[PDB]
Amino acid sequence: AGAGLDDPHKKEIAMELVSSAENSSLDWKAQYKYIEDIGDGRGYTGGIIGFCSGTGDMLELVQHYTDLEPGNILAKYLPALKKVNGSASHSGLGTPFTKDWATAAKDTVFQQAQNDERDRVYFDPAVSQAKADGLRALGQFAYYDAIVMHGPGNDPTSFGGIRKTAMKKARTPAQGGDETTYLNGFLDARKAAMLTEAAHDDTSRVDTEQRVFLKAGNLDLNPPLKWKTYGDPYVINS
Image (cartoon, rainbow, N blue to C red):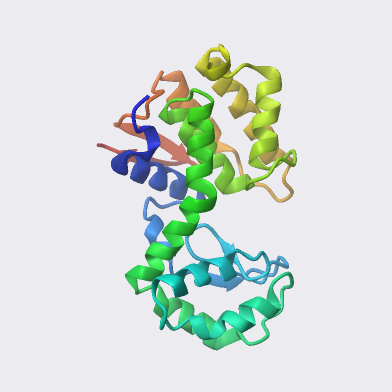
């Protein structure tokens, strides 16, 4: 098609749509300064798509930030991020790290580094796989929203495992299948994945947002967009 969800304006709509489900706000950029150890064993989770000290991705994030801005105030913590990786340890981090993360969030280059990592791992793989599939922007969005909640990989509840379930039920546009048929199939598989996760939310991001755009025939994700997450309305007018 054309630029689809990669279009600057449509890419921003996509970022508010995820944020309406993630944070109940269209204000996604409010999460650059977020950081806390939620108790789940991942260590410190922060930034715009939950980077973590346990996972290896917060260390990649601030390595990216240090390549962009060598004397930034987080580079002192690189040894510590490296020791801690793979565990929920606070060793050499703790309270200075968390005061420092929030100061760094005022730097536009730290903001750009979080966006670059979001794009590297989630946005550009979901959108490119969706175009490989012959999907227009609503499909591209449905892929992105799914890799943001379920993460990369082929295990059954991660993105590639959800796409594999969908494709067992229905053929892709790239394969000769019908797009809203492939997308009801994806959505069904997504929704199933969600209810499988322990301590789940509701599934409105599919039920009263994504499926709503699909039944309207809005396959290019052109505004006005009206939807609900958790009983609350959202409108992007243009």
